[PDB]
Amino acid sequence: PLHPYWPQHLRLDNFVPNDRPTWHILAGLFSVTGVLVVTTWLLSGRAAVVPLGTWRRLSLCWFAVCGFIHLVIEGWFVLYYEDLLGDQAFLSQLWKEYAKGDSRYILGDNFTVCMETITACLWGPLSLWVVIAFLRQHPLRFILQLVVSVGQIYGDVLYFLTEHRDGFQHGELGHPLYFWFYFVFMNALWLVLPGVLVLDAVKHLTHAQSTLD
Amino acid sequence: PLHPYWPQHLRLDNFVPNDRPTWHILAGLFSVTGVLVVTTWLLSGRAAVVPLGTWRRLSLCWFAVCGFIHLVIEGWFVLYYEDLLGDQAFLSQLWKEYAKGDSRYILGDNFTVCMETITACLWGPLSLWVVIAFLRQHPLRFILQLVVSVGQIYGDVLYFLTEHRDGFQHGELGHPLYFWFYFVFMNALWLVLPGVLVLDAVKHLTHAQSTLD
Ligand SMILES: CN1C(=O)N(c2ccc(C(F)(F)F)cc2)C(=O)C12CCN(CC1CCOCC1)CC2
Ligand SMILES: CN1C(=O)N(c2ccc(C(F)(F)F)cc2)C(=O)C12CCN(CC1CCOCC1)CC2
């Protein structure tokens, strides 16, 4: 009615629609991610102590991206979820757009705020320590890769179950953009890749423990 | 009024007070924990491939205790939280007693049910695998100790934050038994010991990675 979010009966007063077009936000976000991924490729080649494999340099790109997303994008929510509706700022309009796939991000849901606080505070800084560790070949490098990836999967599984328990009321089911892209896909990225990185860290640490015997 | 839980205005109909005295439940639980800890001490001494240190055998006692609690006690909640009020089974009277420090366990809270579901399904069976692994000196033994310990702390931190965000409405503040013992202490056990076990697993795995170089 006055707003696009779900369920439709919510009385979300103080809401003001996005001032910018939606493509400035998604074009702008794509650039900063692009700059980061390419420069991570440059920084991996130059500043590494040993020649990293191609899939290893890509792995540092993933951790560099996650570090920025948790620290800056999700950090903004944890600070300003109280006044996110009706705010004219780049990150505020990103969340107003994203929250159409899950209205819990505008309502300041108790679980969502607490989960995001841990993600922004821990897995942001630790994602940067994984990147630094692999360049210098520090012994903690595979242990940190495990601790961050396990921490992300646990938060992501709780995210999907708690919504399923409510019955997906915070977003129209089966919608192409708001459901299958915003809710299913980009949340499932932190469910599948990280699972591949858990299997990798286990393999190298299992061999590390076997050689010590 | 008709019930002892908080906040006092809740209309918790279909509630029937505990049929047994409270001390049968606490005495009964103490015994099974006692039997488990002592037999873990016996099983550690006999069936270990190498002579374990004293603190290592105690560590297997902790994991054996955790495995039983998650699988059997918290498994019961995940199955029967729908009709926990008014039930007469032994474990139902345990939760009716425990839920006086946090009424979310009788209300079937969305976060609590989903957190407990993961606690019972994964962190119970993994706790048993830590115990088996250390007896046989399998290379995964310290990796599982790290994996098991990390998410228990993650679940515990989320448990305490979400209650703080609500303002501790689900239990009277400052009460000696219901607050400081049920809510603060026994939940803080999974906050502090597991943190000591994380530092232990890191210490042995950091050395494992250093020797492989
Ligand atoms: C609001 N978001 C957001 O805009 N992107 C996003 C989308 C596209 C790009 C790209 F391609 F342009 F670069 C970059 C970032 C996200 O990933 C989230 C939504 C999903 N969450 C994942 C959390 C992880 C912890 O568990 C809970 C779920 C993070 C923030
Ligand atoms: C209902 N409970 C319960 O009765 N005991 C309990 C109390 C005394 C004994 C003892 F001493 F007699 F042996 C044994 C067990 C618990 O520990 C919990 C309450 C605390 N939770 C901890 C979870 C962990 C995951 O994060 C969230 C918190 C587990 C169940």
Image (tube, coloured by chain):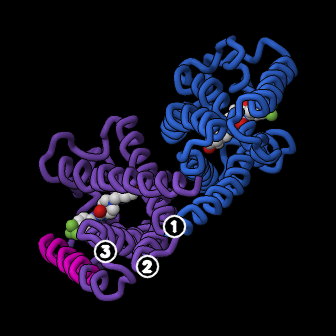
Chain colours: A purple, B blue
Q: Whole-percent x and y of residue B206?
A: 58, 65
Answer with the quadrant where ligand 1 appears in the image: bottom left
Which residue in the protein does label 3 denote?
A: A52
Closer to us: A17 or B56: B56
What residue is drawn where x is 75% and y is 33%? Answer: B44
The amino acid on which the numbered mark 1 sits, given as a three-letter code, is Leu
What residue is drawn where x is 30% and y is 68%? Answer: A56
* Left or right, A173 with reference to B130: left
Q: Is residue A151 above or below residue A168?
A: below
Instruction: Find the magenta span and give its range.
Output: A19-40
Which residue in the protein does label 1 denote?
A: A122
The quadrant of the rendering that contains the N terminus of chain B is top right
Which residue in the protein does label 2 denote?
A: A132
Confirm if mark 3 falls within 8 A of ligand 1: no
Observer-side mark, 3 or 2, equals: 3
Q: Are marks 3 and 2 on the same chain?
A: yes
User: Is A36 within the magenta?
Assistant: yes
Q: Is residue B166 visible?
A: no
For numbered disc 3, what is the local secondary structure?
A: loop
The amino acid on which the numbered mark 3 sits, given as a three-letter code, is Leu
Closer to us: B174 or A27: A27
What residue is drawn where x is 50% and y is 41%? Answer: B111
Q: Which mark is residue B158?
A: none
